[PDB]
Image: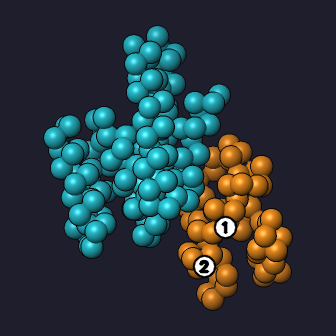
Chain colours: A cyan, B orange
Amino acid sequence: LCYDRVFSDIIYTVASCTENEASRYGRFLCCMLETVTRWHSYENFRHVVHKWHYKLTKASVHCLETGEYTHIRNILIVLTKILPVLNLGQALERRVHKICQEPDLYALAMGYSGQLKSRK
Amino acid sequence: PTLEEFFEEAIEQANEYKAVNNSNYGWRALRLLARRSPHFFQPTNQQFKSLPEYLENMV
């Protein structure tokens, strides 16, 4: 239940960070995420971790395709921190659209897109 | 301000030029809803389209 509530409500907690508390929040998020993916692999657990990843990427695209400067900045630095198929493609397309639509946010978006292309 | 000295208007105003349309206040409301308002971490999960919609319901 704790992991559920941490993976679900990600949106506003991310939106409410002072440009580096988003980094400190992504650090712990990626730590517990790599914990889950480590002791993940088992069928029901595979389904529930699929649901977690789905809710996470859904909140991510929802926060990216809209939700001006503070939201997109915080979610960009967080997605960079948790960087280590269809969901990945959709997130990459939305991030590329947000990047091409555009200062420093464009640089962060280009860096995240490059990291995603490398980790493709 | 503890949830009542801060807003003081949202309850009294409930969207062209309102107060829940400004991010410089909506951000601080999200910073204040973190310390208090136990219904913040509550698993709502209803996919509110915009932050003003989620914010007005939490006031």
Residue A112 place in picture, x, y as percent? 26, 51
Relative height, residue B35 to residue A87 (above, below): below
The residue most toward the top is A42
* Label 1 with label 2: CB-CB less than 8 Å: no
Amino acid type at mark 1: Ala
Amino acid type at mark 2: Asn
Relative height, residue B5 to residue A65 (above, below): below
Residue B28 place in picture, x, y as percent? 63, 69
Q: Secondary structure at mark 2?
A: loop
Any part of residue B28 in sight: yes
Relative height, residue A40 to residue B28 (above, below): above
Task: Tell which of A44 and A117 is nearer to you.
Answer: A117
> What crowding class fits label 2: few (fewer than 14 Cα within 10 Å), some (14-19), or many (20 or more)?
some
Residue drawn at the location 23% of the way across and 44% of the way down:
A116
Q: Earlier in the sequence, mark 1 or mark 2?
A: 2
Tell me the residue that label 1 is attached to: B29
The numbered mark at residue B4 is none
Relative height, residue A114 to residue A84 (above, below): below
Residue B23 place in picture, x, y as percent? 56, 75
State the separation of the CA atoms marked 1 and 2: 12 Å
Any part of residue A58 in sight: no
Task: Tell which of B54 and A81 is nearer to you.
Answer: A81
Tell me the residue that label 2 is attached to: B21
The residue most toward the bottom is B17
Q: Secondary structure at mark 1?
A: helix
Q: Nearer the viewer, mark 1 or mark 2?
A: 1
Residue drawn at the location 16% of the way across and 41% of the way down:
A118
